[PDB]
Length: 153
Length: 153
Image (tube, rainbow over the protein chains, first blue to last red):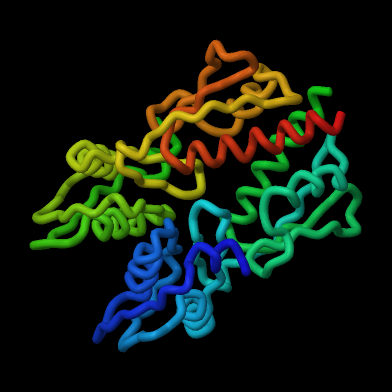
């Protein structure tokens, strides 16, 4: 399975409430499973009722489908956003060729999922990153540094 | 001032409660100021009472001193941990000289504060990163990539 699913394990999740912010349900979930969590300020819905017998990965997928959420896990923190926070950004390094940049982005983070997708575009020496804000920021910072190292040689 | 202080601005903070988790006070603070926030699972204290007329930077420093917190802001998210989560980690690149690594770590993140401190140590081609977990992880990932780029040449 995924690293996130492998970390969440197989112990099922139980909660009940008459009304709590979804932020608080997500927080209490992640923390039950010992997984550091970030929740965007856009995740402002309310949750009511009960979950039981639910496998953790299924809890997260069902919360995400109903509330229109996309998550991004980088082995350290689970970042939870609204799906509407996904954007596109073009990265065009000056000193480093884009094929080599990919070879460094691809062996240290997912580059295929809807939460963080990287692909070469037609624009010369250019890639488009499509993902949640933490994805864009991290790939943009890494690329800038990699480009700065190529400029030194 | 700091980028964080510059972002928080000068509008003062007001809250009252008979009892809320400090996590919820920090969340409501950051969100009042439109600053994305991460709060570690270790920040499990309770808060009682009232804040008023308090300038935001002073709110954060006073909450941090009482509750033994250290924060780390990277221009995107404010990460809040317990000060006891600060650790030391040694980074020893294989292909890239440590002086050049610094020249790339230093122009894209703070390397001087108690929350994220980087310095050369005696161990050959080595630096010690002392900071909160997000700091160690980010500097370690960036270094690994920079080292992978140096190996290609």
